[PDB]
Image: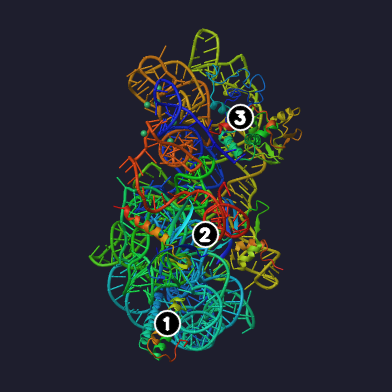
Amino acid sequence: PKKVLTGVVVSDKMQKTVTVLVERQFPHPLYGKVIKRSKKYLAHDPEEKYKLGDVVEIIESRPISKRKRFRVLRLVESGRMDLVEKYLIRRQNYESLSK
Amino acid sequence: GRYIGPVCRLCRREGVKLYLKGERCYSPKCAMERRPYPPGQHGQKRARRPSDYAVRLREKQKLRRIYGISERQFRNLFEEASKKKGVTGSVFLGLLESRLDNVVYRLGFAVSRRQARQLVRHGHITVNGRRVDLPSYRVRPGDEIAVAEKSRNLELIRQNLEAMKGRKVGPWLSLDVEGMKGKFLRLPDREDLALPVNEQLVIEFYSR
Amino acid sequence: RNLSALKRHRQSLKRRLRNKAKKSAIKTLSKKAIQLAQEGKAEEALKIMRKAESLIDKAAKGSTLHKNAAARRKSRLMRKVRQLLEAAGAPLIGGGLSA
Amino acid sequence: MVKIRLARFGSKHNPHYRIVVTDARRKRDGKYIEKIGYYDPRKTTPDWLKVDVERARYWLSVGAQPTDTARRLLRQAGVFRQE
RNA sequence: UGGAGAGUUUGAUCCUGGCUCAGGGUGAACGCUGGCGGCGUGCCUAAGACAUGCAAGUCGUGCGGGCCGCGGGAUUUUACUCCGUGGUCAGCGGCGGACGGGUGAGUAACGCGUGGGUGACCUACCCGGAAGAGGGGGACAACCCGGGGAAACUCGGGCUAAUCCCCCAUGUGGACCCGCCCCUUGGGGUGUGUCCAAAGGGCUUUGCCCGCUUCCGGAUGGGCCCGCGUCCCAUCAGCUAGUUGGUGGGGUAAUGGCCCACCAAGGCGACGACGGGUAGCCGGUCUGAGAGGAUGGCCGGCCACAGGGGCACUGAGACACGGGCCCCACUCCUACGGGAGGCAGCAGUUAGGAAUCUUCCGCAAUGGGCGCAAGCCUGACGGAGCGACGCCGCUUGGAGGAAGAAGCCCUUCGGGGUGUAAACUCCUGAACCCGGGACGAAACCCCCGACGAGGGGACUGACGGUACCGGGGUAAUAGCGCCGGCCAACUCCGUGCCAGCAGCCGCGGUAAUACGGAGGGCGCGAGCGUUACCCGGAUUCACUGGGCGUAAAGGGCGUGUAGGCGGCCUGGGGCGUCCCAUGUGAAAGA
Ligand SMILES: [Mg+2]
Ligand SMILES: [Mg+2]
Ligand SMILES: [Mg+2]
Ligand SMILES: [Mg+2]
Ligand SMILES: [Mg+2]
Ligand SMILES: [Mg+2]
């Protein structure tokens, strides 16, 4: 069955496209503890419809670009800017890590 | 393979009578009557207090030296016995005891295991009628172990099979003396054997 | 040191040539048709399309252009032509279009 | 064109074939689509030929050609024998 | 059904802790030694270079010729010409050359593994089903006649067949545009319009066989995409312009910045981007009590490569190991203009190296390509050969045989040891000789039947005069390591911190069970040792299963970012977690 993934929209800065952060969590093969881990997907939003902070389902799809390979199936809930907030700060930590 | 050298000479060293000659090892020596001590220049100086290791060694030496099977072959049989279901110490005994060359001897067709082994190599033995020249051949229960009718003549087959006329035989064996043949009824139960040998120690020698 | 199936080469060359040839017609004729529609030509622009259509189908009879590379070409062409004609006036006479 | 054919198992001077459906192009002893029988030419056992005839009939139904010698064995187990 | 530890820091002790040994393994190599067989296995190094032979063809039942024959005819005049047939050689045309076989160079990646997606696709030959093949026309090799080149070869001119190419027809049908319906990514259905088929051959000749064409399905094989998984270095921290997305093209069988134009300004990264190193991945293999560690040779699956680098053509399929073009490096021929070539196919040579095989036999079997078949091709393969490289089986005798030869060794001079060992008696009879002698092979095919089912018949064995069976028959090979402790096995000489041993601890300075020899002893045995490498023990990277006051180890102290962790009660949800069913988990291996 075409994979269905649910995540948070963290970018509408592209035409007909959204970046979706999908968290995943599981037992660590050796050390046991349940650990989180995530991935951004670029998903197809043809009616520039879903916006920054929406939770969406993402569905395994016939390719649209190099790297566009999922389409936005539906919307789960609006608003969730905390999640976007989380991602953004984590992103800015990065400056405070080089030389 | 197989040993070939001085023998009622470990009837010695291993401390105890192995009948390896059999015929003589019954009568004023397995060499072991005249000198019940280890061989060589030192063999009757005061016994060294032997190590936990030494002990385990000699004991397996003893057991193996009884059936004159070689270390390689002995070891394979043991590993076979370990991985097999049931009490490994015993099973091993069952298995050594299933070697044709030993059974040929247990049935009395020969007076020793080394002599028995030759009768097997030289075509003098059958199993269920069909001929078999492998000492290592595994005898299973129900198998009939004949002298080869062609061999039934020789001064040896005569003498030994005659000698058996009076003789009693293994609870796990049967032997029709007249028709020069035996049956292998079941594999021997530890109790059926009277071996001068503590097998639990042998198992122990194959730990470390 | 003399493998007699370099005969395969000899034929390949002949075939290469026969193909090259068929395809050249197809291109130069399609060009011609869509050029004519770009100028709003009922009769003449379809008249030619109709030939090109045919010439393609024929090409797909054997090895040249087999398949539905055929089909692709036909589609692309009778889209192009059709649109270009309504992009000017004039609709009618003849042709391989379902009106 | 897929095939019912022989596939060599066993050992040296000890052939045992497996009767297998497989693509024509595939190596002799390679990956097959189904085992559907076996065959020991030296008949060393009572059990020297065996064929899943319902299965043989299916593959034939979908158009696999047996080797000449495969069909020999097939017939012998009565794949073709009718009414 | 599974888990052993020991030596070594001190005068002694307990503890930390490293080093070391005992076990298992190997595509090994090296030393001493070496009898037989079966089954495995054998360039780990230079993906260095390669002499020679062989490794892919086949079809005359698609077609027309050339050359060498033979035989019939027309004329009764011998020239000229028609027909039939046998060699043989290519050519046109098909199907195969994309499989099979080789290697691991590159590749850290959708390459591989595993589970999914394709409404985004392809599939020659095979099977099933529906419907067809009616007219015309053409050319290019062969062959013939010329020219250029040393050679490779090559340029022109003329003739000609076909299942070669084209045109018109028929349109079961299918393709495309537009519409409408169902369905939902480009999936079905339908209506105008347009467009698209074909090839003949054989005959046991009016009726069958091999083919051809369109289309719908099947089967097998493949492309593309996605989730998850997949080594070392952070003393590599920022990276990115087809870059990230878009709209429209192009290209493909098909999606896609795959490619292009135009617009937008984006994408990626401490959950490690980028960079560097190393590396084919897996099924498995070895080891371990297990968790784990290590590994990917043989066999099977996938990938990638074919002197190095580009690239396309042809085709169902290749961007093609034994096809093509160009650049480069090499070797060869050259009449100096130019040409030929590519063992990581089987053998084999040479180089490198500690080291790795026969220029064997056969298409008899299995499997593959073409063929209606007979058949042909097949260094795939089935065998044999070399190497104790590995595993397994077997031999070098068996029973007698002294209070116990000789020699050698010890000796408190009584004796003690090698030792039932030898001698010697009988017995058996590896080797070797004679006789017979396989299975592996019943199909294709032919006959009967009906070219079906079924029945009958014949041909065929490289291994091989081998295996195996019967008869005869000789007492017929033993080596290597070790004996201070760990670790099984002790004595005499020699030697004097020398010569030497040595895995660790340590032996040797004139009485050495530790060096060298000898007697004797322990261990294993056609082997035994050594070196290298992997796991073990090592709970010594500690998830299972470790630690940090003085043994190595708390950051000089705070603040608080990410992150990790989170009191008590109730309700929803059901992501984690748990349960049932089910699919998957190929074969090999276990
Ligand atoms: Mg010390
Ligand atoms: Mg100290
Ligand atoms: Mg000390
Ligand atoms: Mg220690
Ligand atoms: Mg510690
Ligand atoms: Mg400290």
Q: What is the distance, in whole Å, between disc 3 and disc 1 at their CAs? A: 96 Å
Q: Amino acid at mark 2?
A: Lys
Q: Residue at x 61, y 61 (%)?
A: D70
Q: Amino acid at mark 3?
A: Leu
The residue carrying mark 3 is: B63
Figure quarter occupied by ligand 5: top left
Give the camera-side residue of E297 and A61.
Answer: A61
Q: Is mark 2 within 8 Å of ligand 5?
A: no
Question: Does mark 1 fall on the same chain as mark 2?
Answer: no
- Using the image, name the chain to which the residue with label 3 belongs: B
Q: Is residue D39 left or right of A61 when viewed as pictured?
A: right
Instruction: Tell me the subunit letter for badge 2.
Output: D
Q: Nearer the viewer, residue B159 or E327?
A: E327
Horizontal relation, residue D52 to residue E358: left or right: right
Residue C37 seen anywhere in this rendered image of the structure: yes
**Which residue in the protein does label 1 denote?**
C79
Whether disc 3's CB lies below 8 Å from ligand 4 is answered no
Q: Chain of mark 1?
A: C
Eye-nearest disc, 2 or 1: 1
The residue that appears at 58% across and 35% down in the rendered structure is B74
- Residue that badge 2 annotates: D27
Dot 1 amino acid type: Arg
Above/below status of E440 relative to C15: above
Q: Quadrant of the C terminus of chain D?
A: bottom right
Q: Quadrant of residue B67?
A: top right
C75 or B7: nearer the eye?
C75
